[PDB]
Image (cartoon, rainbow, N blue to C red; front, side, top):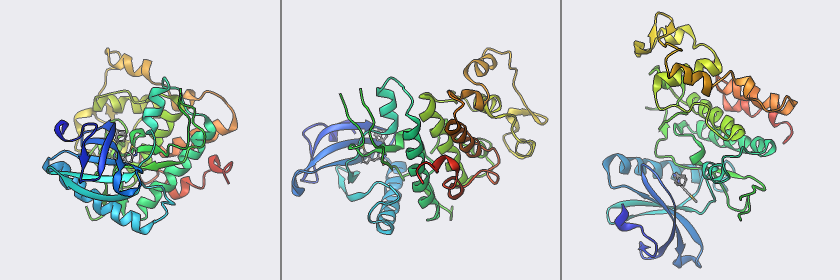
Length: 321
Ligand SMILES: O=C1NC(N[C@]23C[C@H]4C[C@H](C[C@H](C4)C2)C3)=N/C1=C\c1ccc2ncsc2c1
């Protein structure tokens, strides 16, 4: 990786790297000047030369080629791929240049939360976009703030003040069609290995929204049974039917979760977490509307869980309507 993507390098005899925008498990993303197109800047995704990540990159190009053709204007806010190429055995995908991810923006503002009016618009766009994926037999499976990106003209910089937050959605290398990729936004049916599909995206959007509103993550765990105990503290006890169905019966004793809440980590889930409604900062009706939508997105059972077509109909978005 390091050898083939430093500042000053030229890719495919026209893309001159000028900055590194970020680094991932897939590799790197660089900002480049496109010398054969007036000097317009672009973003270039540099994928590791590993079989896992090259098969994902090839799949990602197939998805982006389809989404970009189905939606030429990007009405549904999937990032647009301009071309791809190979560079010293690395797949490089060229994109339109966007701005900060929503995660970088909060992070570099001291983890301030977003304004509620921004959250309302950002949530509408994330829902409208991921619904468009779902209507094309797709599941993103890797929805998170790092993968939601502003379009640079949406904010100032000096201290970043967000102005008008048109967002785009990126990274389709984990995307899956219905024929036949997580961190702490992982849905319960995924943790429990009950199978999953598009509803797990809805759950991850719900985890994104609460983070927008708090500035910090509400499941700050790196352990899967602690994540489950957190869910119970914030959202209530998991459904008996899901507990009784998982092959992962390592986490439970009878119908209850196997967890000594007076252990040092059991005391951590009490300090770190509390029922969802109490996380609210106002009692204003627009705050009540947001958390109602979030409560529907954080529904345990993936069948009960609100779809995104219904989420677009939620009163929280009437102020835009
Ligand atoms: O497919 C992608 N996956 C990612 N992932 C990352 C993960 C971290 C946060 C953010 C920036 C880096 C690090 C790459 C998105 N970016 C992608 C694409 C992309 C397209 C256009 C664009 N314009 C400015 S940044 C940018 C990134």
